[PDB]
Image 1 (cartoon, chains in turn cyan, yellow):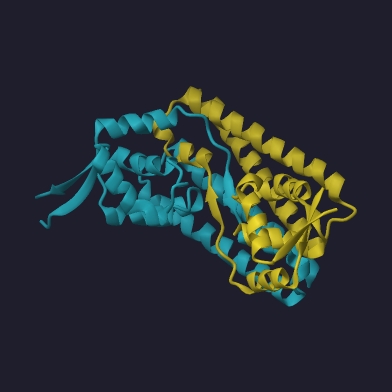
Image 2: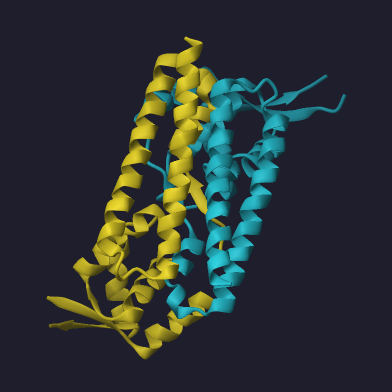
Length: 174
Length: 165
């Protein structure tokens, strides 16, 4: 990461910890399963972010004893406060980096074979994400509510529309 | 990867900084995360390395053979996965910690925002249509399709939420 890391990255972690304590392992998997689709870019910064939040007193790492001991992170009231402050801020515009759309933009410097391949790869990718995501929300959000389901359904709506569009562009090319 | 984007823009023909900015602001804002202001120092860097040349024609930038070779090498690399950050979807994901009034407003705001993006792209298409190529139009159409589906899904969500209350 870098000096330009968004501070909002911290609220991804605090928000996750709002429901219950989680191990590092579990935070990483939720990130890969769910947040890669709508708050990506920050995966490698999970432990650095956890360590910083602990250093500031926003979370605490505890040995839960019972069975095998498990180290888990718990949010503190100071972290709750930072999370709730985040939630009252203005909603930031989407930020997207799509290498694929830029390749299409510069497509006139490629060739038809290569463009066709890239499109087919992109279709296959988005199709896989669609399939993955549903099952991952049932794993991570047992007790999923109407508002939580919006993130899923918007994502699937958007991916599916991208897939449909690309299939049509492919038809036209072939 | 600001470098490659600038060099790609200069492949067709030479451009002023103002020209490059317009492309960033009108096209790339929807699928590139670097702003023109952030990218601007790369012009001097590419100059210093001899990948582009600057002349006082207003200052125009011309790509060199060496810049062309860099760009072609970029086009050969594997395509990196999309990287999306959507504060809106995160608010929804953490929506159990908000309230109905706030959530409804967030959804109406997002519907308006995305409708505005679609209207702006449709306005730009009427501006671009004669020249736009098949491959340049893929970006445009994927964008419209994506935002349109988001708008239609969100309208259904708002209606259902309003029917709950």
